[PDB]
Amino acid sequence: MIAPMEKLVLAGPKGRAKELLQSLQQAGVVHLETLRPEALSAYQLSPEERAELRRWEAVSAGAEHTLSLLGLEAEPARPFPEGLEAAEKALSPIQAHAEGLTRQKQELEEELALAQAYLEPLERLAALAHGLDKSPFLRVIPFLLTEKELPLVEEALRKALEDRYLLAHEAYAGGVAALVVVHRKEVDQAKAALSRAGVAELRLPGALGELPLSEAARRLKERAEAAPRELSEVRQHLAKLARESASTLQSLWTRAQDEVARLKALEELASGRFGFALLGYVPVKAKPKVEEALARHKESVVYNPPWAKPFELLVSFLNTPKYGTFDPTPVVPVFFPFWFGMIVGDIGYALLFYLVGRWLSGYVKRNEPLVIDLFALKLKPQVIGKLVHILNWMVFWTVVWGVIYGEFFGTFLEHLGVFGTPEHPGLIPILIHRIDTAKTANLLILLSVAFGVVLVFFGLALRAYLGLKHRHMAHFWEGVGYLGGLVGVLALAASYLGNLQAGWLQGLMYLGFGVFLLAVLMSRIWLMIPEIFTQAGHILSHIRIYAVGAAGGILAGLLTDVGFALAERLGLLGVLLGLLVAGVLHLLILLLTTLGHMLQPIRLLWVEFFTKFGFYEENGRPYRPFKSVREA
Amino acid sequence: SKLEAILSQEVEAEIQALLQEAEAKAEAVKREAEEKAKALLQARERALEAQYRAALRRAESA
């Protein structure tokens, strides 16, 4: 259709544009536009085109509107070749009919409601009133009043009317539907009595409010009766319109929308590019080749194994450029051992999380609902669940390996020579727990420390690469320069870590280590010296975060002592299962906390990443929140 | 490039239609003149012929 000399649109990160542009040139494409800046020159546009487009928009919108009144909206699937005019035409009869039913249907509901409310008090008024509704010789005034209010209005009336009214009420509960009958002559005084009071007349909607009550009542009664049945019919028809028309609506929708995009596309490019990515034009010899591949860096719109699997997807995301310094990707293969490896549980902690994974590949029945995680049906976005199968793999793996460092843990919390712990007793493994014991514990703590060290190096090294390959001497020196300090830092720790080694051995070396630092920090000149203290907080942080990942972990395993070996009396094999009153609970409590746990790692990681150590999402900047990023 | 080849050829086809029209606007003029002239000689052939026949008539009458 439109773009008769025919469009391809590619979209993306701003930096990639030249490389993208090159990929597009290769494909078989011709007449590549705009190519920096914008504003095509005899390949633009006219409102005629726009008008026709407007017609597609009208249909598009219309299909949605009608779909709306019914309820739901369509999904990307099968458009189909149409007349645009045809599409517009198509929409009209069906929509109007459905819309018509809708229009009646709300009106019916309202009718039903109103009628229901009014009929009974009005009936009460009518019953008192008869003979005198008619008369305008005499006048009668309906109003409803409640039974406290029965003295207050009665006083207002009494003052005006005296006794020249005879004053009537009929009950219907919640008050009595009331009449004053007065002479017609007395009418203002009577109405005024209501006015002083603030008591209100049962005037009702429409013609009905105005009426002789008895007669009015008949009509009102009829509405009450009629409306639910009427509603049923209309509702059936509407329901009927969904059942049949939902596919129809969709096909139209898909078409109309796509067309709307398609049309739009032509219009924006016509004028003025994607932005920083790239359009262009093909004769139909050029047209088949071009779309299919042209290397992932971009989004277009058309006219061992565990370790490979999400990473494989990160290989492409390596390839998106911006600079000669290396790009986002690393996070997923970097996380995994520790991620899993905070989880260091036992029979009742870690080792049952498989069941949950088995409820993501098998499911559950025993409470309300779940059916298939692959079909990800939900209380809050379904969609996501289908997408995050990449995550479903990593999670199934997370538990599996996590269970396993729990089982590493139960090597050292079973076996009778290693600790006092049973090899496999009459209660349960991991029984009178002892990794808590300070010396044993000390080792597990110190275990945590190491991963933090890795991170110190990994980040600053990447800074030196930043300036290396983005060429900034400023970045280079900054990333490199801090390492000048480091030998001396290692000295100071060591004098306590070995209690000896340095700090008075390599502390003479400290005297020279401190100067080396400030040399190239000084080469940039840098009044921006002070910061170096703050860097000192960070190292310790790695330790602490890991430390907690251990400690809170460890604590968790030691909580299964007070979960399942003991928690009232001392827990043997019956009071043990008097703890099982609590035991089921502890699983769900355990569930809550562990969501908490993982996020520290990533926070940790983010400290490094968004100090621009390998990552060009960071406080914005193309690429997008890391939250969204790593998951594929 | 196949696009610009086509852009040339088209504009060039557009030229071909301008010329063809212009030619026709010349031809119609050419043919107008031709009729116009024919019609004029006719008017004077008629009259003179008559003015002859009658004149001589007056010669006879004398």
Image: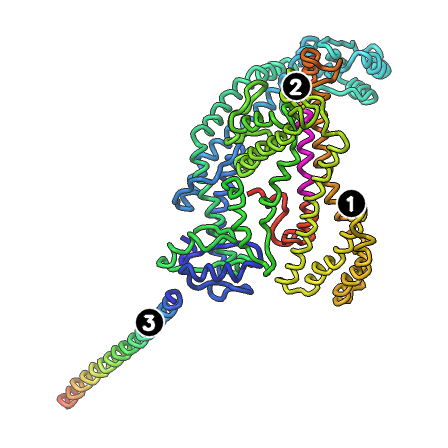
* Residue A139 at least partly seen: no
**Marks 3 & 2 on one chain:** no
- Callout 2 crowding tier (Cα within 10 Å): few <14, some 14–19, many ≥20: few
Picture quadrant of residue A341: top right
Which secondary structure lies at badge 2?
Answer: helix
Q: Amino acid at mark 3?
A: Gln
* Chain of the residue under label 3: B
Question: Which residue ends up furthest to the left in the rendered image?
Answer: B60
Image spot of residue A294 (x, y percent): 45, 55
For the stretch drawn in magenta, the main secondary structure is: helix
> Mark 1 touching mark 3, by CB under 8 A?
no
Mark 2, residue position? A584
Residue drawn 61% across and 39% down? A337
Q: Nearer the viewer, mark 1 or mark 3?
A: 1
Numbered label attached to residue B16? 3
Pick the quarter of the image with the C terminus of chain A. Answer: top right
Viewer-nearest of discs 2 and 1: 1
Quarter location, residue A525: bottom right
The segment highlighted magenta reads A589-604
Earlier-in-chain disc, 2 versus 1 = 1
Instruction: Give the residue type that dot 1 points to.
Output: Leu
Residue drawn at (55%, 52%) of the image: A318
